Amino acid sequence: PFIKKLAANDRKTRDKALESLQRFLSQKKKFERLDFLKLWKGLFYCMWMADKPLYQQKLSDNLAALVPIVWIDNRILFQSTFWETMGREWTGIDILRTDKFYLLMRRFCAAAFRDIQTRSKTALLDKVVAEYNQMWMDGPFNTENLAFPNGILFHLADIWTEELRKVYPEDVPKADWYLPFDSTIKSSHNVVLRKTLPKRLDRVSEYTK
Amino acid sequence: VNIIKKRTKPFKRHQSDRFKRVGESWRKPRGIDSCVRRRFRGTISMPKIGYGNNKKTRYCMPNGLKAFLVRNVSDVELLLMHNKTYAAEIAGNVSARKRVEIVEKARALGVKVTNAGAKVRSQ
Amino acid sequence: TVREDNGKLYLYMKTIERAHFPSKLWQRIKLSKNYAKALEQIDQQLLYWP
Amino acid sequence: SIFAPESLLKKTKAQKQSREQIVAAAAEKKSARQKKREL
Amino acid sequence: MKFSRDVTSSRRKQRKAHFGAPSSVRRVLMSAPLSKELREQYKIRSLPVRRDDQITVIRGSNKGREGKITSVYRKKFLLLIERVTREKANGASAPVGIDASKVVITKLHLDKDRKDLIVRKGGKV
Amino acid sequence: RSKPASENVYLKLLVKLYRFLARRTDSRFNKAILKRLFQSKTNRPPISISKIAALTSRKSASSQNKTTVVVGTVTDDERMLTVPKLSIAALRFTKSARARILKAGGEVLTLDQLALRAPTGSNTVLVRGKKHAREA
Amino acid sequence: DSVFGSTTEVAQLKKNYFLPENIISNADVTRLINSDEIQSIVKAAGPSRVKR
RNA sequence: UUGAGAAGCUCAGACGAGUAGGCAGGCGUGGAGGUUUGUGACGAAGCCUUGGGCGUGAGCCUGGGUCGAACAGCCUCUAGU
RNA sequence: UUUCAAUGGCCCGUCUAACACGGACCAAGGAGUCUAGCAUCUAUGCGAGUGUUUGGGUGAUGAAAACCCAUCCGCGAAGGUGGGAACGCCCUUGUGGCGUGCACCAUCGA
């Protein structure tokens, strides 16, 4: 009843429906994955239809800060559905539009690192990264789903440590920040995705173990 | 680049000077009895690919600008970015009024109109 | 593109995200008389274009 | 603040490898081609 | 367009039935538009042309010359008006054929037949 | 052969992709994928869903994660009752083959989606079909 | 949607009609070549039109 | 450095008669659909020319005279070409 | 362009060295076209299938077009061993080794 307005052809209607989703999403209940897969087919097109470079790079942040609005239980469900729906239809783009769906990925990967910082003050981060790592093990970095394209993970390696440093300027503590990228290059059957992934990664071994 | 021609005399079909039924446009002879086909010396020459002209100074008038048929007032507009490599040749059936308005605008675009003077006596 | 309209030169730009709206497809910027100002106004509008 | 088209971010990284890996074989060529000019 | 299979659109069939129509068809093909002062009092767009009407010529080189029709020449498809006469070399005068579609009727030669056509065809007296 | 005999302008596109991939990489896969798109329709014969399932899954049944790749048409065999979990990548799929792979199995790809999954063509099988009509 | 249907669903106003599909999955071939899937693996490029 | 009609652009070498024959690209004529916000009584088509221009060529564009109602370029289809 | 000078230049086509045969000239006409059958190659659509047009239904805007289609019917209807396309893992970088080996060809099975 709500999504088919997010794919309107008027930015005065698309955005007018976006801020009311902030009311719709902060509800304290349980959401099923497909319901977040149908909602994430609206915010794809809410961002697929984005005209100006000073609006789409503001729309991305309004999508990025939408994650802390999600309830604590389904906050990790909401990002898992995005990385699926940003890997299911990444081949449908062209170069004149990938440039704007890279920054949405850059924000959401960074918006994850921000939420671990928020969750690290409630409970120890060693479990918070693991269940976040779990979300990485059934989303992009899952091995058995060969359909997840390379262009996501090549860009997911370049923005991994740099927006870890951006959200943690003082010092990021030791955790399994790179464990997704180690289990990926070890057994994933995309041959180039295990060969040239280390050549793209900027992993920092001084603080990790 | 200075324009050059490998030949200036066109080719003229054999014995198209004697007979008035035979036209002057070139036609390669088809008989092996022919003196011309076997290319006996003294007979006329033939069109071959040897006389092909330079692939850059082709289609160029002796000035250096290639031609372009402008048959209305929005056909000279395309020549705005090409005024130093094209000459706006006006088409023949264009009226002697629609002609006098192409000239007054091609002159603003600095384009050479080759035959702007037709039907146009100035005062 | 750049194309004049009644004395003053304009700059017309299009994008993918307005392609399906042929009325609103092309936007417009009016280029200043100062020739060095107009070059510095094309670049600031056409940034990171090829 | 327009940022950048981050496609052009990853051309400026692959052109730090293209420059370095051939500007290295510029001194190592010019120092090499002083041996053979004598030899 | 036309949507009848019992009308003809070929130039051949239409341009033959015109030039070889009999002299009763050749009457209603020679009709004249009424003047703007008669178009509102008879409510008739056009009348077929009678003899002794009161017309004015709108088109042609004989522009605006008023008169009355002398001999409605149904054969060569033209009216013949009073005193609009091209000269001849010999000294006599010749009549100028004005097309029946060019004249504008200013006063009808009202008769019992025309009135019984006027009163039914959209108007009155 | 240097240009396809066809006028399918969705197949000038593939040739525009694999004759780029032939010269910017060191794989002879792309210099074999391109070397087949030029071949005429009688030179790219069909290959069934059973011969594909027999080629990969035999001897040791090495069918771990390799994408079978035929530049032809993946037709059907209905004498095959159960279909294994396969993954193919061809130009054309017949509508009874594409519904007999997905019903219990994997992925159906065009050579577009192949070039974004194995850009140098590793972990693949490059099969053909039988050219033999036995008299024609 | 009932005259032509879909690519995997029968058009309702036509017996045994399914909409065709494509030999290229993405309808745009000069925007795979420039993707991150290709330009990571390719060998070092040569120059443009070469010097004489 | 922009030279991406990737059916484009660019670099370098060798070669050049040609019969029967084989292959390829184009030129022109009458009609048909689409297109040129197409040309035309301020002169369309045609015709003539000791005028100019292009193409290797088939051909095309044009100035002057004549003349008086229609006509052409581009992409396809078609043949009593 | 007209002409002059110098140098060259056996009349064209059909024939079989010359010939012969055709040629007074000019204009317009004028000759591998249509159809059925078979085969090759290529293109496209679908594919163990494929083919609407004998018909029927429909078609208000050339309604002989386009569009839809029942019942027949026509054409068709899983052996090892060597190479060998390609692709992994190699470590003698490669070389070579190592594994899976498509079409096609030999070899022994039926």
Image: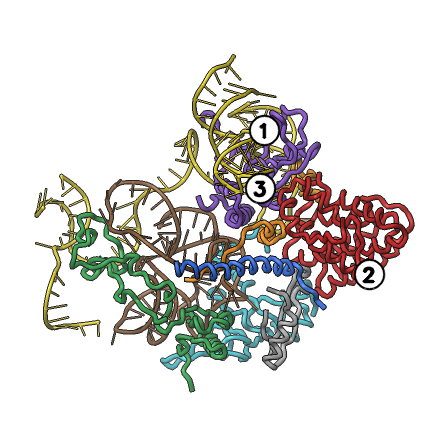
Chain colours: A red, B green, D blue, E cyan, F purple, G orange, H brown, I yellow
Task: Name the residue tied to disc 2.
Answer: A16
- Are discs 1 and 2 both within one chain? no
Would residue C32 be found to the left or right of residue A49 on screen?
left
Mark 1 or 3: the one toward you? 3
Checking the image for residue F55, the label placed there is 1
The answer to whether the residues at label 2 and label 3 have Cβ atoms under 8 Å apart is no
Query: Which quadrant holds the C terminus of chain B?
Result: bottom left
- Towards the viewer: A137 or A5: A137
Label 2 or label 3, whichever lies nearer to me, is 3
Q: Amino acid at mark 3?
A: Gly
**Residue farthest right in this picture:** A28
Q: What is the chain identity of the residue bearing mark 3? A: F
Tag 1 secondary structure: helix
Give the vertical position of E28 relative to I81 (above or below). below
User: Is residue E104 toward the left or the right of residue E85 in the image?
Assistant: right
- Could you tell me residue F77's position as x and y percent? 61, 27
**Residue B97 at least partly seen:** no
Q: Please, what secondary structure does the residue beneath circle 2 have? A: helix
Say which of E25 and A43 sits in front: A43
Tally of marks: 3
Q: Is residue C17 left or right of residue I90?
A: right
Image vertical order of residue A123 relative to residue C27, above or below: above
Residue for badge 3? F121
Q: Chain of mark 1?
A: F
Classed neighbour count for the residue bearing mark 2: other residues with Cα under 10 Å, few (<14), some (14–19), many (≥20) = few
Q: Is residue F52 left or right of residue H78?
A: right
Dividing the picture into quadrants, the one containing residue B49 is bottom left
Q: CA distance from mark 1 to mark 2?
A: 56 Å
- Residue F16 seen anywhere in this rendered image of the structure: yes
- At x 42%, y 72%, the residue is B87
Residue type at mark 2 is: Lys
Q: Nearer the viewer, residue E36 or A111?
A: A111
